[PDB]
Structures are given as structure tokens and as C-alpha cells.
Image (cartoon, helix red, strand yellow):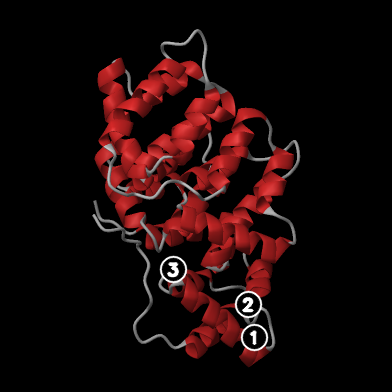
Amino acid sequence: MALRGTVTDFSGFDGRADAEVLRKAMKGLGTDEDSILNLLTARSNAQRQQIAEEFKTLFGRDLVNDMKSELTGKFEKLIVALMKPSRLYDAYELKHALKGAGTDEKVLTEIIASRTPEELRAIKQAYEEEYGSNLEDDVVGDTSGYYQRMLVVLLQANRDPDCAIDDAQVELDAQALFQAGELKWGTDEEKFITILGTRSVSHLRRVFDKYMTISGFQIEETIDRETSGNLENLLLAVVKSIRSIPAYLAETLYYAMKGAGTDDHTLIRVIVSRSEIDLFNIRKEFRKNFATSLYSMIKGDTSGDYKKALLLLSGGED
């Protein structure tokens, strides 16, 4: 499976015409929500920015501000998300997560655990350019403890490259982890942090397997037994991301629509953020792991223009 998103550039794109469509959908009393979502869900993010620019050049009005005025609810939240340039969306989500003692650790974890060193470097740059603070400084100010240190490790965007798998190191790391958790009276967190936070992805997939054999336990189980709270949640998100970013995000989506209340914010972020990267791959995980379409579950748990847009974004029959 090469990585595939569910949204692509529209062939025969006319941004000027698309701009004309959105203006008509909003000029006058009432709003044509349907024309808006059909158009936007079927343009790529880059194309959405071009449309936004044509709208302002034709009309001297701000497309995004107009849609915020005209729209409401979850649907408006999802259009606003869709409109955020791809290069800026993770930094936007991270900035809104960063709120002193009210910080949303869950967002921090999800994005920082699942993004590549390359994505992370681009995010730190965008964040700085847009907000005039340093992403790493704000995270440190808004978090503490081992959780904080793991986030900082990951924020270095410095994980070992997927080079030839030093097979001797594999067993060593696997034993180190065994001695730091199950064998220890307590836990050596720093050890988990360095190995899980810094070794290559392909190396760690080998370490994980070797860990089951030498220990009887999957590394995820040892994490749940040796750690707690935000650290635990982080280490699990990193291990799941090492195993498969798509599988990790399939599950995130799963648990967004399961449980007492729907996590619309998580729903929106994962569909939008991954729409042009690996959302198909995620679709295929969610299927194989949860016994339903991403589609079906979005369909059953959401309603409205919001629903119609998600489903247009998600894609996927069965």
C-alpha cells in the first residue's frame, strides 16, 4: 500500500467560475449550503486557496469570512478546516490546543506522535511564521514531566533514518526495554523515551516483535502496566504510529464516533488533515479492524450538510 489520500486536484479546474458559484450561494438572503460543500469537497486544498484568491480579486470580499458569517455549527467548523492551507493546518490545531493549564494534551499527542520528522519541521516553521512564538517553547510552557520530555524528543524531528537494520541492536534495544519495565522494580521512563522516541521506524518494528518473544508481552501492554496518564497515551500513540500511521488514525476516528458523545473536533481534524495523504489507507485499516466502512460510521453518527461533506470527503462504498 503506497500512501493514498481521498481528495485530488480537480481536472479542468476553473477557480474563477468556482468563485462565481460560491458568491451566488451566499449573495442574497439565505445560503445554498449544498453548492458550497459539493464544490469544496471536490477541490483539493491548493485549489481551495486559488478559489479563495479569485473570490477576493473578483469581489473584494473575503471568502472565508463570508462563509463564517453564512454558515453555522459543525458544518461551518468543517468548511473552515477545509479552507485552512494544508501547510498551516497542524500548526493551527496545535496553537488552539495550547492554552495554559487548559491545554488539550490529546491533540498534542495525536499530531506529534503521528507526523514524520519532515512534517514536524514544516509545522514548527509554519507555527512560528503564523503566530510569532516557537512551537517547542509553548509546548514546554504548557506541559510537564516525562510527557513534556517525550514531546520535546519528538519535536526534535530527529528520529534515526530507516537505514539497514542493525540486527544486533534490535535484540539489545528489546532487552533494554525489558530491563526498564517488566524486570524493574518500577520503571525507567527515560529509557522508553529515548528508544521509542529516537530509533528508526523500521528498526522499532523489529524491536517490537523481538520484545513479544523475549517477554511474552506486546510493548503496548508493557506501556499500559509501567506508565500512566498523558505519558502512557503518548507512548501508545507513538508505538501505534511506528506500527502504522493509518491504523493509529483509523482507531482515533473509531473512538471519536464510539462512546457517550461524538468527538466532532477529532472527526473533522483527521478527515481533513489526512484527506490528501493517507485517508484511503486509513479507510482500509478502519474496515479491517472495525468491521464497517468509515463511511457507514460517519453516516450513522453525523447528520446534515456536515454529514454530506464528511461522506463526500471520506469516500468508500464498503
In the displayed structure image, the side of residue 118 where residue 217 appears, left or right: left
Looking at the image, tell me whether mark 2 or mark 1 is earlier in sequence order: 1
Residue depicted at x 56% and y 41%: 153
Instruction: Mark 2 and mark 1 in contact? Answer it, CB < 8 Å.
Output: yes
**Residue 232 rendering spot, x and y as whole percentages:** 52, 27
In the rendered image, residue 145, in percent from the top left (x then y), is placed at 66, 29
Residue 83 vs 234, above or below: the answer is below
Q: Mark 3 points at which residue?
A: 41
- Label 1 element class: helix
Residue 55: image quadrant is bottom right
Three-letter code, disc 2? Leu
**Foreground residue, 238 or 291?**
238
Residue 29 lies left or right of residue 170; in this view the side is right
Q: Which residue is drawn at 40% across and 72% down?
A: 42
**Location of residue 26 in the rendering, given as x and y in whole percent from the top left corner:** 61, 78
Q: Do the residues labelled 3 and 2 touch (CB within 8 Å)?
A: no
Instruction: Please give the label number shown on residue 63.
Output: 2
Q: In this view, does 193 lie above or below 184?
A: below
Marks 2 and 1 sit apart, C-alpha to C-alpha, by 7 Å
Which of 35/168 is in front? 168
- Residue 56 - label: 1
Closer to the camera in the image, 222 or 111: 222
Q: Judging from the image, what secondary structure is the residue with disc 2 in?
A: helix
Q: Within 10 angstroms of label 2, few (less than 14), some, or many (20 or more) residues?
A: many
Measured from the top left, where is residue 269 in percent x and y?
51, 53
Lower position in the chain sequence, tag 1 or tag 3: 3
Task: Please tell me which residue is depicted at 25% across the width and 55% down the height of the picture.
Answer: 317
> In this rendering, does residue 85 appear at all?
yes
Does residue 237 appear in the picture of this structure? no
